[PDB]
Image (cartoon, rainbow, N blue to C red; front, side, top):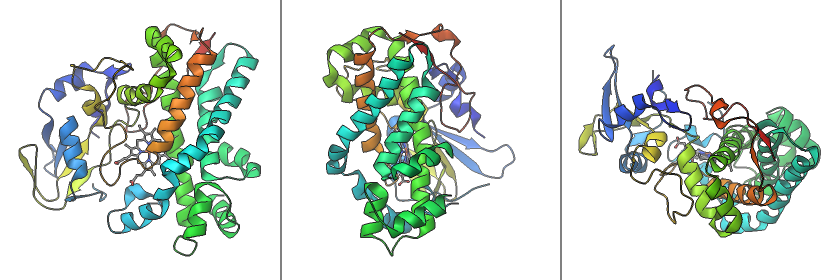
Length: 354
Ligand code: HEM
């Protein structure tokens, strides 16, 4: 439902979706059957206003333990507080060199296998999955099978008995009794499944985006210090996480000048908020600060953004440096993108040569 919020022209918005955004940053959508009233939050400020408000929950409208996205306060707060330290700046700094080496491992395989390569399946996917295992602290003997399968309750209970390194070891060590096997397995699942999906798509589609702007491909090679800026601009432009689960108002609340009634559901379009403003939409990695909501906002703000930002920075900076002659093996116009859907936005394959 609301398929219009996912209509794209390759990487850009479809004219049908652009026309919808012209109806204002907040659009009232009464269902034809009269069963409910829905809202589209299409603007940067409105999306942030909706997602920051405490007067919305994430009820199901007309469930896995450890899935933070399906919890509201106070239970959401309880679980997020236990896992949040795994993403501290000190955690990411200690992890960076090991992530760099994993990225280098996969670009080593790439340069040795020789061209061409299907970048999505053969590089981006394995890279994101391997970085995920390292962050989680998966034992090396389990990573091969854990990746192929994406068992979990079995893996979670065992690691919980003998806590090791990574996020799962930290949680089990500091909150052993407060988190169950199923909840710990759920934390690991979200990281290995949706998180990898979104990260691998940024790696692949982001590479294509850089290739379609060769002046910036080289610029990031000349000036690797733009990496952090480039990541923000890439996730903004891609918007692989296009739309969010509905937020239902728990009471009458005024948003963007209009009154959202209790019980009405609001659908935030990160795609539209990140891309609808033609002024300053061009892809430009020299932008020192991007206006985007690709990682969400509020209490549900992407808990893995620190890892995602670091992994993508390392991946893109090392890629342009080790493969300055990189190019699509087919005309970029022939790349296939997944048809509109609530699923993560991604291309179907990315054949590359160099
Ligand atoms: C390092 C890889 C990633 C990890 C570990 C990760 C972990 C999560 C977690 C734990 C949540 C739940 C937050 C909560 O409800 O409290 C989440 C939701 C989200 N993630 Fe991912 N994520 C990852 C890659 C991404 C990337 C690359 C993006 C950017 C497109 C992303 C955009 C989101 C957004 C926007 C939400 C919030 C959805 C909503 O508000 O309904 N994530 N992620």
